[PDB]
Image: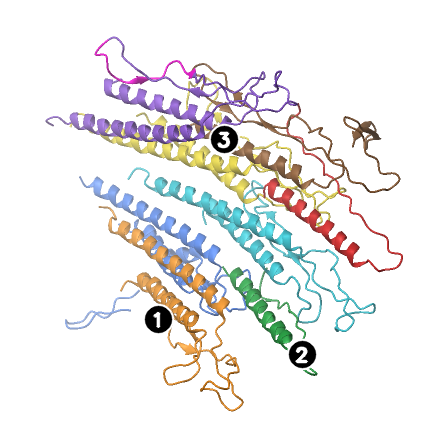
Chain colours: A purple, B red, C brown, D blue, E cyan, F green, G orange, H yellow
């Protein structure tokens, strides 16, 4: 895999994973329970630069998805199970505006990397006609 | 057509039937021996989708 | 690309919630009716790397056993139960259903 | 020879004529009593394929020379007169344009094959 | 007609006929008489699946628009002709709220089929540039 | 696309009914006036199919 | 002029003239007098097919705008001139809801013919590229 | 750029097309009360498998065995309409409209992808012909 295709493809993968996390947040906002019974903790991705040994630059890797540890806004329904003493359901802490902006920006970055890939592919296929 | 539209439609029809009952009931004041009429409704069979 | 599925799920399941509310809401002025409260469940998709997606499956945890409010009709055999009470009724198939 | 191109030639020409007919149907969507028309494409195409005399050829200055609208069954009567159903006309027009594009592509590809054989 | 153009166009034509039945019923609510002198009997459309022979599925046929057999709700006017013994005018049996809900449903189905046609049409144009 | 016309008909005809009642109604306190009652007629459009 | 261009453009012209007549009616309803002093008569257009010798179909012509023969609803103002014996002014008989529906229907037909023209333009430009 | 990639992508095109035609049928026949013999319409789905099961390695998709979806067949209640049984319930086909919207959306996208793959392979092969000269 040529280096520049690898860089832009890693960008594409990272953007797809970021958009997926944003969609999962925006979809499970207002979700009382998980499988076992616990709040849905809002999810974020971690972007880090790739190619750690060598040139210190190139590509983006989204290893280690993490959780946004904000204090998980509460509501009061003291007849609902999943409510502790001081009946307080846990109610995922997803901020819809932030997630919508994340989706928009991720789509735009995805487009930019796709279209870098197209430009580079044309560049290389033209290089193959060097001379002849 | 999705279920929500028709469920709300049958709610609207039930309220209309109740109002028909009330209007008849109110027109028949000063009708000797008339007995007031009360509409009684009921829910419909629940379509289960996923058992607990 | 599979993100659309998750989003679809949410949309589809939200309609189900709507449906519940509608049936929950048309049934005002239905005697002794118990509102069917509803919730949305996150469903993680545990997989081989980067657990990033969750679905939005709709659910009805049960009924709202909050006593509805009483109408005085003075009819000799119209009955109102106290809180958490039920009248037992021989169901269609034959078994003790419970009603308010 | 070189009449292998005849079939798609006639098919494309017939598609264009049907396009004109359907555009006439759309244009006359609201005139009273228009009584919309159409043609049966399969029958017309068969008829053109299955089926022209050159005149007398004496001394020069001799002037050589030469030269079915079916009714669509309507639904939804109007008694405003007309019988053009917009939904049917629109679907037929879109399909006809698509098939015209197909015929154009096929004829162009046959011409490309013929021209590529020659170099 | 190509296959999906046929299916979606049949959906559109059926929805249009349903909408016309709804509009006619809604407009003739509270209409004492017909031409011959008869209650205006409310109308309904029955949707059959098209394509009985072959694959048993695809498209919708709505032939034989029929009459809704609700009981022709009556009003009392023994001064109006058209009233029998125990003077009772015939007064069409149109359920107006049912017709409004039916109109919205028909419109939404119409628009959904428009949208599927749009997407598929883009697909087909892309198809024809197959090679050339 | 012709549904609109049917609806148009109804609306237009309804407006005329309004006028009737208005003429029916402004004539209160008119000596010996005879109220002109009104009605709506279904006019079927019997044609070829559907 | 190309033939299908002629058909669709004639439709555009006829629809524009119909919309103009409808606007003139809707604006001159509620008009007491003309220039010479007479009722304003609601105007209507007459639609006919075109290209009579040959093919018996194709395009719409709007020849002979006419004045409607509705019975010229009267009002009573026997102090205002223009009122005959038994003082009665002439007061145009424009059906406003009919004219509103005319405006919307004409606009919709205009859109249909516009877009048909655009489609045919694309078809012809791809026809030029036959082979080359 | 082998010739047995035309078969794979063409089969993918056919499978996507059949899935899309089925989803269009589902969306059109929503609220189709009756079948021709007289039965509620059952919303259908298509089953995708890998083509050429035995040996092979990987190659192509097959849409054999169109099946019938097991949604709970939602009901309505109109005991004035025929086709409603005892406890009048019109059987009302079970179409998940938004799911079918998305199905058509993705089917179009995958069809477009495979069309493109066909074009790209043909360009590869035509430039294969220019080997040497």
Badge 1 crowding class, 10 Å Cα cut-off, few under 14, some 14 to 19, many 20 or more, is few
Q: Which mark is residue G51?
A: 1
**What residue is rendered at 34% in x and 53% in y?**
G119
Question: How far is the residue under mark 2 from the one under mark 1?
Answer: 62 Å
Cβ–Cβ below 8 Å for labels 2 and 1? no
Q: Chain of mark 1?
A: G
Foreground pick, E65 / G28: G28
Q: Is residue C13 visible?
A: yes
Classify D2 as above or below E72.
above
Left or right: residue G5 versus residue C54 is left
Evaluate whether label 3 is on the same chain as label 2: no
Badge 3 crowding class, 10 Å Cα cut-off, few under 14, some 14 to 19, many 20 or more, is some
Q: In terms of secondary structure, what is the magenta stretch mainly? A: loop
Foreground pick, C41 / F32: F32
Left or right: residue G109 versus residue E37 is left
| Membership of A60 in magenta stretch | yes
Q: Where residue H48 sits in the image (x, y, percent)? A: 50, 28
Question: How far is the residue under mark 3 from the one under mark 2?
Answer: 81 Å
Q: Chain of mark 3?
A: H
Residue beneath label 2, please?
F29
Q: Which residues are magenta?
A: A54-66
Evaluate whether label 3 is on the same chain as label 1: no
Q: Where residue H128 sits in the image (x, y, percent)? A: 23, 27
- The local secondary structure at tag 3 comes to loop
Foreground pick, G35 / G94: G35
Residue beneath label 3, please?
H63
């Amino acid at each position: 895999l040529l280096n520049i295709f690898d860089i832009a493809g890693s960008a594409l993968a990272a953007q797809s994973k970021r958009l997926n996390v944003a969609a999962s947040n925006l979809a499970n906002a207002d979700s009382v329970t998980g499988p076992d019974g616990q709040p849905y903790r809002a999810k974020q991705v971690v972007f880090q630069v790739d190619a750690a040994p060598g040139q210190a630059t190139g590509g983006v890797k989204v290893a280690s998805v993490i959780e946004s540890q904000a204090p998980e806004k509460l509501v009061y329904e003291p007849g609902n199970p999943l409510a502790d003493a001081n009946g307080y359901v846990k109610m995922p802490n997803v901020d819809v505006v932030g997630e919508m902006v994340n989706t928009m920006s991720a789509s735009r970055s995805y487009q930019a990397n796709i279209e870098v890939l197209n430009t580079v592919k044309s560049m290389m296929l033209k290089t193959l006609t060097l001379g002849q | 057509m999705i279920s929500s539209l028709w469920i709300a439609k049958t709610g609207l029809d039930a309220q209309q039937t109740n109002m028909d009952v009330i209007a008849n009931n109110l027109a028949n004041v000063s009708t000797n021996g008339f007995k007031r009429q009360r509409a009684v409704f009921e829910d419909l069979l629940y379509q289960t989708i996923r058992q607990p | 690309d599979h993100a659309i599925y998750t989003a679809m799920g949410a949309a589809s399941q939200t309609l189900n919630q709507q449906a519940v509310t509608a049936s929950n809401l048309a049934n005002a002025s239905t005697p002794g009716f118990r509102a069917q409260l509803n919730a949305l469940r996150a469903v993680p998709v545990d997989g081989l790397s980067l657990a990033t997606r969750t679905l939005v499956t709709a659910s009805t945890p049960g009924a709202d056993m909050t006593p509805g409010q009483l109408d005085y009709t003075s009819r000799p055999l119209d009955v109102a139960l106290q809180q958490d009470g039920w009248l037992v009724v021989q169901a269609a198939d034959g078994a003790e259903g419970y009603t308010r | 020879l070189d009449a292998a191109l005849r079939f798609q030639q006639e098919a494309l020409n017939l598609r264009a004529q049907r396009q004109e007919i359907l555009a006439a149907n759309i244009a006359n969507a609201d005139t009273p009593g228009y009584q919309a028309r159409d043609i049966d494409f399969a029958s017309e195409l068969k008829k053109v394929m299955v089926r022209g005399v050159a005149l007398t050829l004496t001394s020069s200055h001799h002037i050589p020379a030469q030269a079915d609208l079916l009714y669509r069954v309507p639904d939804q009567p109007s008694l405003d007169g007309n019988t053009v159903d917009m939904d049917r006309e629109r679907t037929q027009f879109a399909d006809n344009s698509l098939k015209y594009q197909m015929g154009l592509t096929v004829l162009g590809s046959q011409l490309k094959g013929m021209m590529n054989v020659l170099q």
